[PDB]
Length: 84
Image (tube, rainbow, N blue to C red; front, side, top):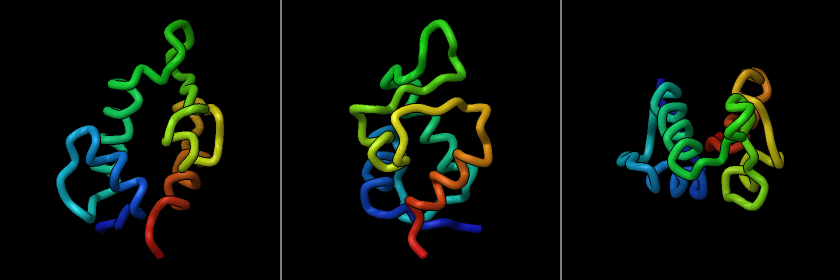
């Protein structure tokens, strides 16, 4: 199953090496992980915590922070950034 990122999510994924217009959810997740890691958006002392205020990721997700453990919340935030 392929999903289609909306334009600003697509820009975000391409910034960390993604190539296509449509993606498996696995690939979306890999590039979001790459983005958080490369920009060092996580809390060095509590590494599950992502601080995304002041970054495009937070603008798109609609939150200033979250934990990678919050799966339901993460997939809901991703769903907001996919074309219907």
